Image (cartoon, coloured by chain):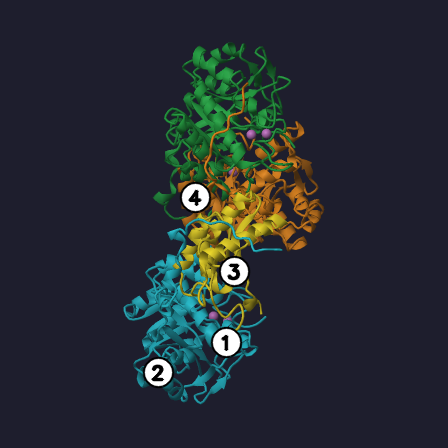
Chain colours: A yellow, B cyan, C orange, D green
Amino acid sequence: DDGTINRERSVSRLAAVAVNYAKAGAHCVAPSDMIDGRIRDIKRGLINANLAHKTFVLSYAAKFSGNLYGPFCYQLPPAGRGLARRALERDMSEGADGIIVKPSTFYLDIMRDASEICKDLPICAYHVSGEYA
Amino acid sequence: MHTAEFLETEPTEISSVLAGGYNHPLLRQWQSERQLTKNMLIFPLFISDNPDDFTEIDSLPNINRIGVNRLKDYLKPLVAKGLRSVILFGVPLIPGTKDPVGTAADDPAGPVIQGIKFIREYFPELYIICDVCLCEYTSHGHCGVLYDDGTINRERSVSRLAAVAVNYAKAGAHCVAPSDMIDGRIRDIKRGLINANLAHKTFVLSYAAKFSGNLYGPFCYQLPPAGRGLARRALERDMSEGADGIIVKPSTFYLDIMRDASEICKDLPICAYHVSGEYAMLHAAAEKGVVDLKTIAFESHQGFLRAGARLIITYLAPEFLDWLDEEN
Amino acid sequence: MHTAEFLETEPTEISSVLAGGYNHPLLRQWQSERQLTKNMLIFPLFISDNPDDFTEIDSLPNINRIGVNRLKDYLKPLVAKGLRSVILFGVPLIPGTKDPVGTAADDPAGPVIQGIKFIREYFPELYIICDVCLCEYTSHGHCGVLYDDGTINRERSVSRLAAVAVNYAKAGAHCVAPSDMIDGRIRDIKRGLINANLAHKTFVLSYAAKFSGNLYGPFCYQLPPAGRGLARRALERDMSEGADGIIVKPSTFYLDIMRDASEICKDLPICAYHVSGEYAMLHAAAEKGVVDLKTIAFESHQGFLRAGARLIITYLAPEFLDWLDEEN
Amino acid sequence: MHTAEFLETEPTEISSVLAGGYNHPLLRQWQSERQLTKNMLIFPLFISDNPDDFTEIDSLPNINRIGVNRLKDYLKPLVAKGLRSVILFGVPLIPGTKDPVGTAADDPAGPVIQGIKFIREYFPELYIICDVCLCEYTSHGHCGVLYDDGTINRERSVSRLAAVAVNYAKAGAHCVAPSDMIDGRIRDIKRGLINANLAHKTFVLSYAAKFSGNLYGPFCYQLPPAGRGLARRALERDMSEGADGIIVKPSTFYLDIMRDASEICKDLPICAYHVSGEYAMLHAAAEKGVVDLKTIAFESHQGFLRAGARLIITYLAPEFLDWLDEEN
Ligand SMILES: [Pb+2]
Ligand SMILES: [Pb+2]
Ligand SMILES: [Pb+2]
Ligand SMILES: [Pb+2]
Ligand SMILES: [Pb+2]
Ligand SMILES: [Pb+2]
């Protein structure tokens, strides 16, 4: 009510769509929310639906906030470098198969942390439209 | 009808809730490993040999080619705005000063040395950093003393570099930043200072990691933007050779490399350099309204601090000494 | 009746499900720390002193003993197929050229040097790597300059090796790979190049880990297939001595050792070498239909890349420059 | 005349001389992190349902399809030669025993269980390891219990696997090695054993790292020869799930992976498995005289020990129990 995101509900709803996509024929599902614990839930959902062995959970473990998406919710502080590590380490244990870092160029150091933390996971770089433009 | 499906969850793990640590605007100050202050900013200066000069350069810049007689006005406002340091780049325009050995480099009557003496007197507060390269004082324009119609003659160019470096320091400069990339020039510059008993007062700020890309000017020894293993061996090398601080450049495009410097040269101040290319790129982007300059300047400059740096060589110094003063 | 029993399980842990990360054929490209490209392949060449030679060698090979006049045809197709490098091995067949000091080694009129000049002109694109050993230019055939009816006279053999190494580089070779195993030959070859002002253009590709086994030829200083501690001290030694890259050989049988090289010499390109024995072994196996060559060539060569290597010296180069082009 | 040039060296660094540590034949025993003994060798056995069987299989093998009545002769010599263990693989040839749930798997009157009872009595010294898979007892031949005209039904196949695993152990087998690769089957097999109070006597020897290549048979869940990150997450997973030991397979082609296992599963015995493909490859190569079998068997098997393993599942067991006895 006329405030913030209702975690559990939004998450309960997200896992829903995620499995629906996968049931439709999508190979991978990349949740771009940043809402706490949505990988554990999406992972389970896929599991219950026996789709966990064919879907690749490509998480947006590190999504920061800056003037690079559009000019001028849960979204990490461009300076919070300690959070981005705890969030990467969290999604990795929760079941993430791959991790996305975004933006990219402006967060190369953070792409470096991902490389050490999520060492056995494919790391994905995203060139946000802002950088592109 | 297509109804919204909602899966059935589990009680929220306490280890999935980081949120409460970055919810208030002050907690995003509390989450920064390091805050951007004014004594971090380092303003570069292009001191011309024409004592009346003040020629605007360009690509998107707002920086110039000043002269020893316009100097007291340019610097004055800035310094009052709390400027603590500047990195001198001399620009000899006289019709007969460049040559096969950048002889005019340590020239007691040159832009740089006649800039280092001006500051030490009209602004004894300021801290002086001098770039040390033969780039701009050689006929060929190469960064070093060349061999027969080929490559740089290492030892010679190095023997010549340490020379200028100590000459600057004898002139009154606090720090000497060699921007060569010619192997072993820190050991040599360090010794030189030692022989001249100037090693305990000069700060060797090395350009340990200088890569090559379209960010200096559009379109010698200079690291491959991909060679990440070399940049570590070069940082580790200059550190043992005596470097007191390390410079990474460019900056934004080498944040990961600024991260490696932070781990490798952990007890050494790491300096981030916003190359003119990036500077002229933030600006151009700002005019085409792709992003708000001020918004992209902080993001980009706090990334330096996040990535590892505690110092910053940027042309946005004039603007930051303003901004940093602000609150709401 | 014997009925199938089925125990009663627990809900699948999320941390037991890795499966979804390697299910689609593209995810097995996405799971490779490094993909096999063509500029990784390094083709060895046995340049004979008989300028018209093209004698097939053998054990199961398809490689030869070519001469400076057949060279432009052998190389041409390959290079067009995108070949980027070759490692020269000279084979002097003249009746009076071997001896007590491998004098004919750096011979300006030899297979290797008269091969290094041919390439630099008819194929200026190619990258030249030269093996550096006195093995094939000595009467005794030993890898070094011997003492009285015994062992290798270290210092001398080394003093002689650095000599040839710089001679090659003076001739136009880009890289020199010393395959001796004689202690301290990298420090010496590195210095030599330095004195000759050729250290900034020559790539010292050392054979840091050369073991001994039935894989070179069927049946001197050479590491024990079990000495895993020596191979680490030798890698760590050549790295400090100046090695720019490291070669592991054999390859398949020393993948673990390629793994140690990857951790020890982390900022140095690691090169995998498929010894003729392994090559002639994959082939023999292929003919007796134990495995499909092409199937076992990729597995075996991606193991090099997985294990740590980013470069590969193999005789299957002709075949890979083909294969790599393919899709379905 | 072309005279041999000899550069001028520096006095030999003491840190370039490793040589004296591997000069005598005994120092190559002294340099091995671990020596190959007989209680390391693990002989696989293909026990057929036809009690009189002894059918030679093949690709280059010398191994067979034995039966419970020929068993006492095959084993006897070996055991006297000091054989300490065997890994049973049952082969039901009866015309009506395979099916949609590998029901005949834990069959009290099957090759494997009627092999596990034979040994425990006629050779109570031996140590019994049983492979645990539904591969060979299913109509489809898949490694697990399948869903509708597709993939393996995880939970079910797992619920069924733990079942057989405990049945074997109840029969008298000391160890159970699940060769499935179906996620989470160790946690489940471990629990099962626990419920049946057999967890303190059964050794869970997991196939933590089973890759896919042309080395089992020429030409389900099975790791990509390049996925080196998965193999680490899978090893780390089975270790926490209760695995007492880990098996790497194939072996020679995955020595680097045997190296990762050694660091990751440091307090767990690591087992190397020489897949039939490699076995039939050393042999084929030996016949075409590319290498001497005995020479390549030791090199290849000491690489297992060097690479990390302290146990070895190989078909060359008959031969090693011989060889190991030798001296000169
Ligand atoms: Pb320069
Ligand atoms: Pb220049
Ligand atoms: Pb040799
Ligand atoms: Pb030889
Ligand atoms: Pb199976
Ligand atoms: Pb099967």
Q: Residue at x 38, y 59 (%)?
A: A82
- Image coords of residue D324 (percent x, y): 44, 20
Q: Which residue is mark 4?
A: C235
Q: For the residue labelled by badge 3, is the local secondary structure a helix, a strand or a loop?
A: loop
Q: Residue at x 39, y 37 (%)?
A: C229
Distance CA(mark 2)–CA(mark 3) = 37 Å
Q: CA distance from mark 4 to mark 1?
A: 52 Å
Q: Quadrant of residue B268?
A: bottom left
Q: Local crowd at mark 1 within 10 Å, few (<14), some, or many (≥20)?
A: some
Please tell me which residue is depicted at 51% across the width and 38% down the height of the picture: C249
Front residue (pair C322, D251) = D251
Compared to residue B81, the image places residue D177 above or below, namely above
Q: Which mark is residue B79?
A: 2
Q: Secondary structure at mark 4?
A: helix
Q: What residue type is disc 3 on?
A: Pro
Identify the subunit bearing mark 1: B
Question: Does the CB distance between marks 1 and 2 fall below 8 Å?
Answer: no
Residue receiving disc 3: B224
Q: Amino acid at mark 4?
A: Leu
**Quarter of the image with the C terminus of chain B in it:** bottom left
Q: Is there one chain holding both mark 2 and mark 3?
A: yes
**Looking at the rendering, which quadrant does residue A1 occupy?**
bottom left
Marked residue chain, label 4: C
**Chain for disc number 3:** B
Mark 1 CB within 8 Å of ligand 1: no
* CB at disc 3 and ligand 1 closer than 8 Å: no
Q: How far apart in space, not on screen, are marks 3 and 1 (Cα)? A: 31 Å
Locate residue B304, reporting x and y percent: 42, 67
Q: Nearest the camera: C257 or B93?
A: C257
Q: Quadrant of the N terminus of chain B?
A: bottom right
Q: Given this view, does label 4 or label 2 mark the residue nearer the observer?
A: 2
**Which residue lies under the disc numbered 1?**
B292
